[PDB]
Image 1 (cartoon, rainbow, N blue to C red):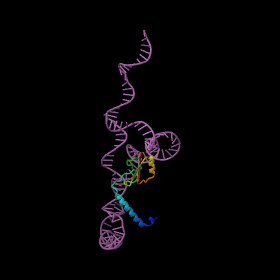
Image 2 (cartoon, rainbow, N blue to C red):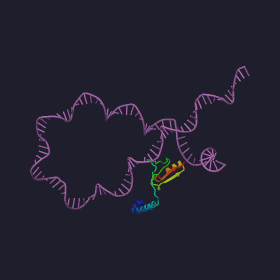
Image 3 (cartoon, rainbow, N blue to C red):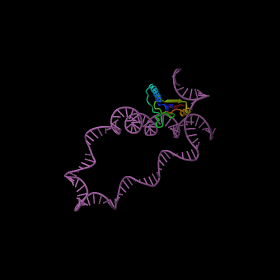
Image 4 (cartoon, rainbow, N blue to C red):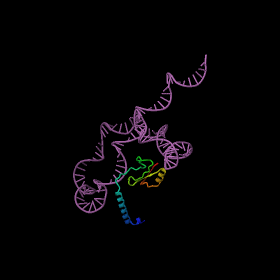
Length: 89
DNA sequence: AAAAAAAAAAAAAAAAAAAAAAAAAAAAAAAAAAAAAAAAAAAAAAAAAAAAAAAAAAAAAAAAAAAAAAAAAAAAAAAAAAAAAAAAAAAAAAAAAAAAAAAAAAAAAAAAAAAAAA
């Protein structure tokens, strides 16, 4: 409600947050976006991989879990944007 | 004779697959109606042909809507930046014909055995 009411302070805080995010992004090394596994494209990746939607590395994570039961438990609870799970055996 | 790798003991971690039974849907492959398309007959509206004709381009000339000039003002389109869609170029691949190595049948002949004759 406070953000909805006061526009100027909200814009200033958003500007500060964007500046901090850009400063964080400046420290990252150069990288290339990767073809991610999806419904339309699999890219020759394993069937047990539950890949994310983020095409950019440095904003994605791989969780190496012990098995398929833990794999299902982690796949049910995660963030599809970033988290990816590769259940081992 | 030294090095290296497989395999097996037993408590641990973690997975995978084939069928039965009924009822509904979804692919995917066929006969079979159904209409384009094509070959080969007779058949019939159009060009030809000719004579005969009269309706609209020329020509005189006024005048009345006009396209260039002048001005003010609105703002469509073009080129430069970026950001997506969609197609040839090139390289890769799984079955698939070709080749080579091992299992089963074959009889020639003899060792050992079993059996019986006088």
